[PDB]
Amino acid sequence: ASAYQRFEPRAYLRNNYAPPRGDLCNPNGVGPWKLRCLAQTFATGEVSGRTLIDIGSGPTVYQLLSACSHFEDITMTDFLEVNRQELGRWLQEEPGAFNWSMYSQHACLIEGKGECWQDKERQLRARVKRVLPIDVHQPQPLGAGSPAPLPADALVSAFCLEAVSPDLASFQRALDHITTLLRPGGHLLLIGALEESWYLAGEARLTVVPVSEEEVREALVRSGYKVRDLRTYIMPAHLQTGVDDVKGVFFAWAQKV
Ligand SMILES: Nc1ncnc2c1ncn2[C@@H]1O[C@H](CSCC[C@H](N)C(=O)O)[C@@H](O)[C@H]1O
Ligand SMILES: NC[C@H](O)c1cccc(C(F)(F)F)c1
């Protein structure tokens, strides 16, 4: 976890959200697939409410695109200052912010409601009230008196848990921890890597717990969830780039019962 102190956001983003992986043009790529999972899931309109929290946002927003048109109060979080600062930059349209425009576009394309992407971003920025520090290893991961209206009506988290946890049980506790933030009857949309064990981000070389679809399911159940959907994307050769050793990406829609 002290490895995360050398974590370089610009190199993360570059490694994982710029082309090839960041070229949204081929619909068989991983970005289109993630974006579509979120989109489909919300267009069901069974995931709805007033507040929502992004767990381990790091320096990224795509995970909230389709989401943001359904929850008026959206809280973002990450363990690192540097990331909370990089999010700041895009939220406030400051100089040198990252360019998500491609992602916004495709969310708009995928949702098919004829929305322009500036309207979409405009809505996201507007609905993101706060960026908060977070440690999922803590049993109240946000702290005590957090500005975050609890309990949240829903949780979103991508590539965090399995990437902050040294092992399967550790991963499992973290899940219990965040689940604490989620109002009962509420919804969790979880996206992560499958059987990934390391991934780079500049100088920082991070270790990952290689989980599996079955492990992830059991884990969601153990933590008190009803699994409404679990889907798997197998990484194609040409998206294997040596910034990691990820084999697939998984997406899960789970309802706390
Ligand atoms: N103990 C911890 N608790 C919560 N987040 C942590 C953490 N330790 C590291 N992190 C954060 O977990 C993030 C993993 S990278 C994930 C970024 C983004 N959600 C995506 O879809 O790409 C990093 O931003 C990192 O800072
Ligand atoms: N967990 C970090 C990992 O390198 C990662 C982040 C985002 C996307 C992807 C991938 F493209 F699915 F491999 C991997």
Image: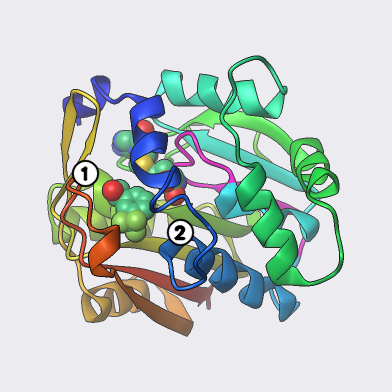
Foreground pick, 202 / 163: 202
Q: Helix or strand or loop: what does disc 2 sit on?
A: helix
Picture coordinates of residue 182 (x, y %)? Answer: 56, 58
Q: CA distance from mark 2 to mark 1?
A: 30 Å
Q: Is 232 displayed left or right of 53 in the figure?
A: left
**Residue 159 seen in the figure:** no
Categorize mark 2 by other alpha carbons within 10 Å: few (<14), some (14-19), many (20+).
many
Q: Is 19 displayed left or right of 35 in the figure?
A: left
Q: Is residue 11 above or below residue 47?
A: above
Foreground pick, 207 / 219: 207
Q: Residue at x 75, y 61 (%)?
A: 108
- Name which of mark 2 and mark 1 comes first in the sequence: 2
Q: Is residue 248 above or below residue 97?
A: below
Name the amino acid, label 1: Val
Between circles 2 and 1, the one closer to the viewer is 1
Q: Helix or strand or loop: what does disc 1 sit on?
A: loop
Q: Is 35 displayed left or right of 39 in the figure?
A: left
Picture coordinates of residue 1 (x, y %)? Answer: 20, 31
Dot 1 corresponds to which residue?
243
User: Mark on residue 179?
Assistant: 2
Categorize mark 1 by other alpha carbons within 10 Å: few (<14), some (14-19), many (20+).
some
User: Mark on residue 135?
Assistant: none
* Region in magenta: 49-61
Q: Mark 1 CB in 8 Å range of ligand 2?
A: yes
Foreground pick, 239 / 80: 239
